[PDB]
Amino acid sequence: ERTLKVLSPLHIGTGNELTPVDIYPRENIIHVLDTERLVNDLMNLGVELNEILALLKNPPGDAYIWKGYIEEFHLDPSDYSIYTLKIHGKIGRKSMQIKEFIKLNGRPYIPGSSLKGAIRTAVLYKALKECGDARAVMRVVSKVNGDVARDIGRSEDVLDYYMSFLSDRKRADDLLEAIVFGMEPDRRSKIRYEPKRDPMKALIVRDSKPVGRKHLAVYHVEVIGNPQPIPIWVEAIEPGAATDVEIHVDTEALRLNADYFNGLLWECLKERGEPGEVFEDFLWEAVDEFYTAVMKYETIEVQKFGRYTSQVRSFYASLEDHSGHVLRLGWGSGWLAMTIGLLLVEKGYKWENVRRLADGMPMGWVVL
C-alpha cells in the first residue's frame, strides 16, 4: 500500500449535511452531538418530550437549538460529543450547516473512485493532447461507427469537433468519454461507452485505510466565480493528514484484454510501444503533466479574484517540492468539459469565451 498525504483541505462528501440539531458550537470547536443520549438525559432531568419536539419543529430565531439546554442545565458538551471539529473561517451567525465527509462506520476515508477519477481526468488530458489529431481519432472511431468517424474528421482537431458538436453537453461529454476510454456500437445511439473495453479497468484503486477523525475539521468555503448568500461549510481532512492506499496495475487484465480494448487511449499507448507495458508509465506521466497545468491555471484564477495571499503563493510553491505524484481530488460531472477547456486555453483561447477556497486555501490537493 502506497502512502497518501493531504496537502490542502480535502472534502469528499456524501451529500448529507449536519444540521444545527446535530451540533453544539463553543469557542472554535463544533461539537458533533449524540442527540439521542442528550434527549434521554434531558428527559431524566425533567424536560418533557413535548418541549423538545416543539423546539425541533420551531428552532429559535437568534440562538441555536441546544444552546438553550446545554447552558440551562450546565451540561458538559464533551459528555455528548461523538467527535469535535476545529473551526476554520468566519463562524456562522446562528445556524451552521456542514457538508458531512464520507465515512464508513464513523471513520473518514478517501474512496478509490475519488483517486481513480483524478487519475482518469489526467489520462483524458494526455490522450487528447497527444493523440487528438483527426487522423488518429478517425482510425479509432472508424472501427466502431464510420458515420461518427466521418463526422469527426472534417472538423480539424477533436477539440474543434467537441466544440462544433456543442454548437446537448451530456451527449458530447458521453460521446467523448466513449471515444477516449472505450466504446461499443449501439443501434439507438451511434456510439456508447463500454466499461469492458476501457484500459482503466486494468488500474486497481482501493479505498484508503481510514483517517483518524482527529484530522477532520470544518472549513468556511468561498467561490471565486459564484456569489452565494448562504455560507458554505464542509467537513474536510486537514493538511498533513496521511493514510495508505492500495493502488497498482493489474498486468494480467492488461495482457488478457489486449485485443478487446479500444478507444483513443489504447491507440495512444499503441503508438508509444506495446500498449500494456506503456500503460503505467503513460498513466503517471499524465498525472504529472495535467496537474501541473491545473495548478498553473488555478493560480491565475485565484489571483484574478484577488485572493492570492502570501499563504497561497507559498502553498503552490510547496506543491512543487514533493517527490511523489501530486493530484487534486474532487472531480464532478463536468470533468471532461473542464479538461477540454484547459486544452483550449493552452492553445490560446480566453477562458471567458470557453472553484472553492477552504478558509482561503485551494481545496483537494494530495500527494501519493
Image: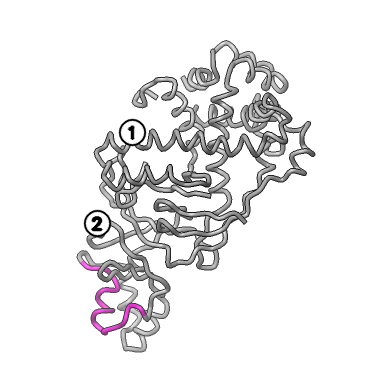
Examine the image and state in which quarter residue 86 appears.
bottom left
In the picture, measured across the screen, residue 33 lies left or right of residue 283, that is: left
Residue under label 1, please give it.
300
Which secondary structure is most common in the magenta stretch?
loop
Residue under label 2, please give it.
90
**Observer-nearest residue: 181 or 128?**
128
Where residue 320 sits: x, y (%)?
A: 43, 42
Colour treatment of the image: one colour
Secondary structure under tag 2 reads: loop
Secondary structure under tag 1 reads: helix
Considering only order in the chain, which callout, 1 or 2, is on the residue closer to the N terminus?
2
Where residue 10 sits: x, y (%)?
A: 43, 53
Examine the image and state in which quarter residue 126 appears.
top right
Q: Amino acid at mark 1?
A: Ile
Examine the image and state in which quarter residue 119 appears.
top right
Instruction: Find out whether residue 325 is within the magenta segment.
Output: no
In the picture, measured across the screen, residue 82 lies left or right of residue 248, that is: left
Q: Residue at x 52, y 44 (%)?
A: 325
Crowding at dot 1, Cα within 10 Å, few <14 / some 14-19 / many 20+, comes out as: few
Where residue 71 sits: x, y (%)?
A: 24, 79
Segment tinted magenta in the rendering: 63-78
**Observer-nearest residue: 250 or 90?**
250
Distance between the alpha carbons at the discs numbered 2 and 1: 25 Å
Where residue 115 sits: x, y (%)?
A: 55, 48
In the picture, measured across the screen, residue 83 lies left or right of residue 57, that is: right
Quarter holding the N terminus?
Answer: bottom right
Q: Amino acid at mark 2?
A: Lys
**Observer-nearest residue: 178 or 346?**
346
Q: Residue at x 24, y 57 (%)?
A: 90
Crowding at dot 2, Cα within 10 Å, few <14 / some 14-19 / many 20+, comes out as: few
Residue farthest top in this picture: 154
- Disc 2 vs disc 1: which is toward the camera? 1
